[PDB]
Image (cartoon, coloured by chain):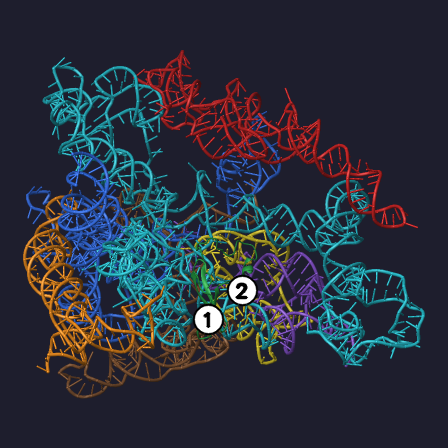
Chain colours: A green, B yellow, C purple, D brown, E blue, F red, G cyan, H orange
Amino acid sequence: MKVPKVIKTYCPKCKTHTEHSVSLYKGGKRRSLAEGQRRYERKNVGYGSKRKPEQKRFAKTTKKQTLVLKCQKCSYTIVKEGMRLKKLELVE
RNA sequence: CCCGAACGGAAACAUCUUAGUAGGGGGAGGAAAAGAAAUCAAUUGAGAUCCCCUGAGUAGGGGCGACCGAAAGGGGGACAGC
RNA sequence: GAGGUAGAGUACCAUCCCCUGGUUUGGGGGUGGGAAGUUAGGGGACACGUGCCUCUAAGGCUAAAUAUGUCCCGAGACCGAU
RNA sequence: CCUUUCGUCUUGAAACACGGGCCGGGGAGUUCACAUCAGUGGCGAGCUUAAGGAGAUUAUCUCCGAAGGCAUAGGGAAACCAAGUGCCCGCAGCCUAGUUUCUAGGCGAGGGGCAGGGUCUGUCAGGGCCUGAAGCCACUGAUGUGAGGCUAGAAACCGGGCG
RNA sequence: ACCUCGGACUAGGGGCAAAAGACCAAUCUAGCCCGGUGAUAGCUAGUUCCCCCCGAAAUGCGUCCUAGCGCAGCCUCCCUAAAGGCAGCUCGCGGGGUAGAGUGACAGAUCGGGGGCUCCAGGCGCCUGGGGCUUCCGGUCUAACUCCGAACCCACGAGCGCCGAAGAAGGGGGGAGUGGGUCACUCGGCGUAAGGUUGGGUGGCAAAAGGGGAACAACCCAGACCUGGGUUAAGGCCCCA
RNA sequence: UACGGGGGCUAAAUCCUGCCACUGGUGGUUGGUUAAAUCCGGGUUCAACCGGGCGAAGCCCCACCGAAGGCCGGGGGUACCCUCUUAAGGUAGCCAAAUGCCUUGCCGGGUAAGUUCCGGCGCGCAUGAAUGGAUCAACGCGGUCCCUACUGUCC
RNA sequence: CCGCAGCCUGGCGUUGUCCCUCGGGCGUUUAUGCGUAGAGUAGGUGGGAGGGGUCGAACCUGUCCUUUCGGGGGCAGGGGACCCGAAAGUGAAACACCACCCAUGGACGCUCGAGGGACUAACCUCUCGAAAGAGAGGAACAACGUCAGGUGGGCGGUUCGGCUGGGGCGGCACUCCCGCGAAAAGAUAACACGGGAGCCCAAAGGUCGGCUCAGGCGGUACAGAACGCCGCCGUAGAGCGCAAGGGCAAAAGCCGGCCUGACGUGACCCUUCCAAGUACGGGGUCACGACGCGAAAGCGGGGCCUAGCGAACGCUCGUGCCCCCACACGUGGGGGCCGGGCAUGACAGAAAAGUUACCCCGGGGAUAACAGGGUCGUCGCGGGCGAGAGCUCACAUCGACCCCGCGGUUUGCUACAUCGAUGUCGGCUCUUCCCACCCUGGAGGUGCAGCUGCCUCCAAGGGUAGGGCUGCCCGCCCGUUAAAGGGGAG
RNA sequence: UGCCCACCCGGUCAUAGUGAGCGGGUAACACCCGGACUCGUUUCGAACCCGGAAGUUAAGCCGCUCACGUCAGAGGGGCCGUGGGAUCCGAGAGGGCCCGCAGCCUCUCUGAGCUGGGAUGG
């Protein structure tokens, strides 16, 4: 697909339809020392089999594409619903 | 007091649990152990330890799965401290 | 009033391992470092700082209150010779 | 005169399926704890004493002992907030005169439907939950769950010894 | 590389094996005994007093699931609740594309003739044969065609009819088994077929004795409180009888 | 204490498993490099120090020598052609082998008949010379086939 | 799927002393600096108009080093005492003193490397020695401990999907969708049939406006059946993204204009999933708010409608706050919500390879193999009919294409019976049955001179061998005989 | 008066349609006049938009006739189902019969526009 860089949509803080910056969604860094991460080593310490099952088989060819819009007039950022696509082209 | 199991359970099973039990080794006594806080808790309080009833399946742990699982305080027993 | 004493590879720290709810927080050990020590230290749920509160280890030793039937008295909605 | 042999598995299969010589004796849904219900009783905005102590003809018994737990308010993670009333239909019973024999009408407990209120959430409608004042204890009972778990039945694996 | 005797040593996930997974005490794809341990069984067999009342399913969805379970439906028992409830029919009023029928009403399938137009081959401008196009006329089929279209089945209202305060629409609660069905008839599909399989509806049987069909789970008659009398059903009536 | 210690295939024995591309040497050269000694110039009041021409042998190069070391494939196509290692591409043998499908290749032996076996010829789908192919002396309670003698195995 | 031994490498400790070249440093020792304008070396910031001054300066004269030989910096004597300005320039001034930074070199005690070397006193190896102790070689290595990484079926535990007309192979009927199945309510099976999806579209989306298609006819240069143009007809025969079904004409089709509603938040409801429980997903109807389109009504939370998709846990993102302790407070760091993404196609979500013919266990006739029953595609046989050949003539005999029947001799399916056993091929012996008659008996026809033939019908009383090859059956063959029939009886 | 006759606004959505022929208009309705302004023609006043308005029943509109399409009625012909039941027939396929219902096609003939709300014309 093709999507323009700027889309006039509603801004919750601006309480009307405003211009926005549109870009793909990117996951953040794993951010070690998380509670869900801390227990991993505390569960991996000692002797035993691979404590947590890990996925090895993959079925879906692609992954869901998500749109991220930022509200220029108030620096707000909104999170949109995902969708399955080949590759979301950001060219206007 | 050291060493240290599998069986099963998770309807599979590997983390986990079954479990510091079964069992090994050492060493006593008629009881042993422990015993005088680097204890608690929290509006500035209590006052060794032990066991009994509660606190309580609460706190908290774990493919958050089966399950495991306190303490503090209160109530009893005798309450000895050098 | 003045002066003095008050326990080291011990606390504590990093790491690996063990276990217990102890979890970024517990205790033990191996390994490496490693203090202060009275004008000392520790502790008061992640770390650090600040104040406030309470204890003083790294040596002892200890009456009773409970664990049990190889045994001895007693009792029993325990059976009558497969 | 009419009549396939017991039990079980089983769509039927029982009669070519299994287990069945005879007799006698033995022999299999129990125990606890929790949860929940029923039935039963005691008390009641309380209930309930445990563990435990004292006295006693001594495990019986009597008194004492709320320790505690459940209910007595819910929402949400929290900071916190935090109700119990108001309409209507209407059973039994009662009252009214007829009782002609009675929904003829009222009163109407209970109950039902619209409400309302507290709470979080949503910017309002809303949405989720709670709220109309009764549970606790004791016995027996039943079922689920955990313990060998109705009875009996395996290859397995492990520890320690003995060849 | 003979054979054998007495002594001695090698221990089980080990020992030995001129090695067959052989032997190691009759126990060897991992020795024995005792203890974990009353291990694990979604499997297999048994499960014991009487009377009486009531009284099923073999289906759907999910499941490393089809030899079991969860949620349903189907049962029994209890309490509350207080006038309606509806397994049938009739009327009224709606829904339908199936049986059938049609193909010039689409989609396709498919047989022939006639007329005209066009091209080619042959023969003497003509004729014949063949090729393409059109028109007209005729016929043959459709689970995946429907211009039409029943019986029929279903919704709702009213009516009829039945049950109902002796024995009660709704609500709550305790306890289950049931998830392998089969056959007969009837309308399908698969397959020629099948006491085959797989669907819709009904009926038994399962759990239903009694009478007939010779005996018999299911075929017909017909639902066993008991004794007795009588009349009858499905069937039968020469003898067995 | 390596003619050893341990580990792996095998089972005795016998026989089959044209080329100078590189090096070495020899011979030579248009041509390039090449030490010591010597000449010239700068520079130094002379010496130390910088560049220019001559510079032997060896090396750079070519050809030959393989009873000099030694070497001597595969693929494409139809035993042969062709690029490269590096020059060519291993002759030869064996075979109805366990290899051959037409099958019982055909024929002969052996019997009345032989789907068994043996041997011979040659159509090699698809042998192509190494942990392979061929090979039987002696040996075997090994397996198959045939003959004699034998004989109640049979009729 | 993995885990643990062992092995290799490296780090740390047992780990000592001299060094040695270089590159790093540690705390020190010191000394070295011109874009232009200007008395002139302003390298860049500070306190600082005072700093030096028998608490020794200006002046010039040389020895000396260096440099962009610009020029400054260090030497005592000759000289016994003087210069910079708060004054002139510089986007930034004082060679007025003392500080910081960059930058060049050497050295001091310590550390690390590229490393290298040496020694012995650790320690190791061996010998002597009763002990004590001594001697010989390697060496701060090795070896051990510990940690990490690589390898690691040497050893240990495990799984080895599901559906299935036995199982495996086969395929996915295992996730969702169209029609048919399917029988005019709904629901309704098949490893039934014909098919699709794991997307694509910033425009293929919203709205407004305009035009009407496929196709055919007549006339015009190139001109053509079909490029364009002018007229006539054309009820969909086109087109609408992707399979099918349906729907659609001033449109949902085609062409332009403007847009981003393919909207945020909170809802109810349909299908999923009938009656009669339920995850997703899709879809519909809303309110609040703001948008966009059009004059407007109004229409727009995606595609004309029906397929285009993923729980817990954990991770990440956005969101405004909330919480972090047995004392409070501060900072950091964490935790929670609410929603989004990261996947599981075995698609209602374990992390998962083969053999066991050395197997073992509890079962299974809910189920394979031999053996009954049902059936008859095949097999054998029969009959109908009759193209054809036989000299003529279908039926003496052969009968093609077709059609209708029988048997349950093999062979195909069926799983009703048997899995706590109905012991499996052949053959031997022995008994019996049947007739679709091989011979023997009777009768007949004949393309029957006679024999030999060929064929039909009746007839099951009797007989129907012996050998070779092959285990058989089957099959080939030998020599006689009347021939050397075929089948049943678990 | 009137009512229907067209018109504007419709409902029914073909019995109301299509095609041809003819008839009707001095109002109504169109045809038709012209574009400077409004607006507008990826050329054009074609069309649309605006300003109009001579002529005119030829279009259209309207009525009528005839054809076809199409709804019904009747006739002829075509074709033929299904519920309910039986130890009825038939081996089966199938069929009859008693109890209840039908419809389908195709030719012939006969009809074939209805109606609400308002300003013109008779």
Determine crowd level at label 2: few under 14, some 14-19, many 20+ residues with C-alpha closer than 10 A.
few
Q: Position of residue A25 (x, y in %)?
A: 48, 63
Q: Nearer the viewer, residue G104 or G17?
A: G104
> Disc 1 sits on a residue from what chain?
A
> Which label sits on residue A41?
none
- Residue occupying image coordinates x 46% and y 61%: A89
Q: Which residue is mark 2?
A: A35
Q: The disc numbered 2 marks a residue on which chain?
A: A
Left/right placement of residue E151 relative to residue B18 reads left
> Tag 1, which secondary structure?
loop
The answer to which image quadrant residue D95 occupies is bottom left
Residue G31 in percent (x, y) is at 81, 65
Above or below for B43 versus G456: below
Name the image quarter holding the N terminus of chain A. bottom left
Disc ID at residue A19? 1
Looking at this view, is E129 or F15 the one in front?
E129
Q: Which residue is at 48% across, 65% downward?
A: A23
Which percent across, then down, holds residue C8? Answer: 72, 63
Q: Amino acid at mark 2?
A: Glu
Q: Please report the residue visible at 57 percent of the width from the left and 56 percent of the height from the top.
A: A46
Q: Dots 2 and 1: beta carbons under 8 Å?
A: no
